[PDB]
Every structure is written in structure tokens, then in C-alpha cells.
């Protein structure tokens, strides 16, 4: 009888957020 057929085959197989903007300027010294 003829041989047996082969066995199919094998099965082939984010960036970080930016830094927050710096705080506003400083307050001026009082009057006189």
C-alpha cells in the first residue's frame, strides 16, 4: 500500500507628555 501524507505545516509568527509652562512673573514691591 501507498505511503502516508505529510503533516500539514507550522504556523509562522507612546511618548511622554510635555512639561507644564512656567508660572507668571513676580509681584512688584509696594508704594511708599
Image (tube, rainbow, N blue to C red):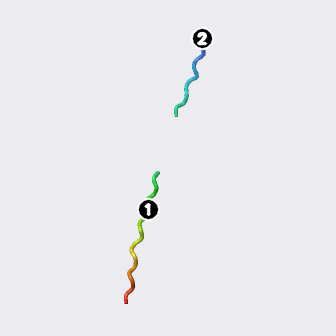
Q: Residues within 10 Å of mark 1 (few under 14, many from 20)?
A: few
Within-10-Å neighbours for mark 2: few <14, some 14–19, many 20+:
few
Of tags 1 and 2, the one toward the viewer is 1
Q: Earlier in the sequence, mark 1 or mark 2?
A: 2
Percent across and percent down for residue 3 are 60, 13
The residue that appears at 58% across and 22% down in the rendered structure is: 7
Q: Residue 24, how many percent across, how many down?
A: 40, 72
Report the number of discs: 2
Instruction: Specify whether 3 is left or right of 19.
Output: right
Q: With respect to residue 19, does 31 lie above or below?
A: below
Residue ID at (57%, 20%): 6
Q: For mark 2, what is the residue?
A: 2
The alpha-carbon separation of the residues under discs 1 and 2 comes to 73 Å
SS for callout 2:
loop
Residue 28's spot in the image, x, y percent?
Answer: 38, 81
Viewed as shown, does residue 29 lie left or right of 5?
left
* Left or right of 1, for residue 20: left
Horizontal placement of 13 versus 32: left or right? Answer: right
Q: Residue at x 60, y 16 (%)?
A: 4
Where is residue 20, by image quadrant?
bottom left
Numbered circle sitting on residue 28: none
Task: Specify the label residue 19 is tagged with.
Answer: 1
Identify whether 16 is placed above or below 27: above
Can you give x and y, in whole percent of width and height, for residue 19 in the image? 44, 62
Outermost residue to the right: 1
Q: Residue furthest bottom?
A: 32
Quarter that holds the N terminus: top right
Quarter of the image that includes the C terminus = bottom left
Residue most toward the top?
A: 1
Q: Contact (CB < 8 A) between labels 1 and 2?
A: no
Label 1 SS: loop
Amino acid at each position: 500500500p501507498p505511503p502516508p501524507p505529510p503533516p500539514p505545516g507550522m504556523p509562522p509568527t507612546p511618548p511622554p507628555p510635555p512639561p507644564p509652562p512656567p508660572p507668571p512673573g513676580s509681584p512688584d514691591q509696594p508704594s511708599a
